[PDB]
Image (cartoon, rainbow, N blue to C red):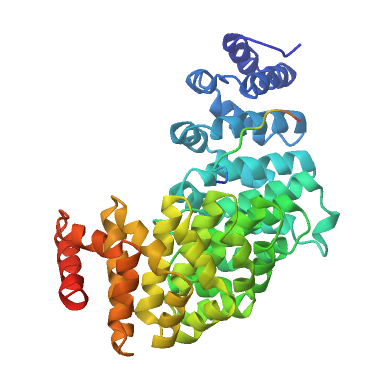
Amino acid sequence: GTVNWSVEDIVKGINSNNLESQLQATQAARKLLSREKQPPIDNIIRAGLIPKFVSFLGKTDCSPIQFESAWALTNIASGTSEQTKAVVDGGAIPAFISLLASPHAHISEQAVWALGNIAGDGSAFRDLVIKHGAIDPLLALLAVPDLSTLACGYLRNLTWTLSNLCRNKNPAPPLDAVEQILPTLVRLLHHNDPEVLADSCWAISYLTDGPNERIEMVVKKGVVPQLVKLLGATELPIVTPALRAIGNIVTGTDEQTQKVIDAGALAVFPSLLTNPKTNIQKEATWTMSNITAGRQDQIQQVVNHGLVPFLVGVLSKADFKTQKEAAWAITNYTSGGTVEQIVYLVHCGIIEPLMNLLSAKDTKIIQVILDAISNIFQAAEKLGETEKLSIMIEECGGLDKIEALQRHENESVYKASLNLIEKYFS
Amino acid sequence: TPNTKRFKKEE
């Protein structure tokens, strides 16, 4: 039928001026272009077919050829930036935007998908899709009282494409585009389909991956409670973007971080900081590090939620990149914490795993640990208890490691190490 | 994570 045509035959059919011959040739192109094993994208491009496909998107009396070319162009646009650029170069962006209004749901959906691929290429094509006015028709497809009346795959496609309009930096998406999209995004973030939740949550993570003003737009929409709820989900595909979004938000101001805490996020961290997925633990610990960089009352809520033992645990045993985030969380904690909070940290057992990580070859983690120890000694000074900490560090082999760090190549490490020797082990 | 671009295999 239309199975395994040559590109040359596809060209012959598409260059006939017979719409039905063109349809069958376009379907044959679609079938080539949708095979998983090496779809001949560049051959189709090189045969000059993209402009014909784009012209077929406008064949209103001819919805099957609209669909077939939309699918063909979608998969071409799914490839490299050069392959996506060829689709854009053929005029596909306004054609696909016009196709969003198709009364045929499967065609509308295919145009949604193709625009998602185009926008997914990068900020430039994302902004170009926005400039051609994709957002209004995309959002109009979701302007129903209850998202649950929409077809499942259709809604997931719309969510995914919207998330690509929220994606990428240098530049971030246009502020008015974000403002226009956000209420619908918030709708999707409360939907019951796990894939819609995951992609909405990714979209929110992109929007919060930026300056405090970007974070504020999201936080002001009141999504933090829902993010915290998703943070506790059982599905890893939902926890991951929820944790990234929460982690992004706490890189913001202390007040933005406070929303995260007020929404109850800290109660999820016993599980997050022991999560068997390495990247969850790492990003939970990174998130903790930006919370312990907060105000003393925020450190206190970390304490109250029982999270210092969990930091001790991650410091004691975790993927090394997670232990690095934990070292940072401790240094931030000891930099901003009260004497009592820092004392509490020692009582939880921080010293020995902190010492054990001074054997790491990573130069940066050593400075982080040395600085935390400095901060802990300064707290010990204020209680006249310096020497007890010196014994503690002595008894677990920490002083041996600090001594040996005088012999470290890095200047700031050898310095900070020799200082620690000069003030507390003399 | 997730996919910047999606290839349509079927349906």
Q: Residue furthest bottom?
A: A383
Camera-side residue: A96 or A294? A294
Camera-side residue: A322 or A390? A390
Q: Quadrant of the N terminus of chain A?
A: top right
Q: Quadrant of the C terminus of chain A?
A: bottom left
- Asked where in the image residue A219 lies, by quadrant, the reply is bottom right
Say above or below: A240 vs A416. above
Left of A261 or right of it: where is A214?
Answer: left
Say above or below: A89 vs A384. above
Q: Residue at x 61, y 28 (%)?
A: A53
**Horizontal and vertical percent for residue A186?**
67, 66
- Asked where in the image residue A111 lies, by quadrant, the reply is top right
Q: Residue at x 58, y 77 (%)?
A: A261
Say above or below: A188 vs A336. above
**Horizontal and vertical percent for residue A228?**
65, 68
Left of A57 or right of it: where is A304?
Answer: left
Residue A327 seen anywhere in this rendered image of the structure:
no
**Horizontal and vertical percent for residue A128?**
49, 50
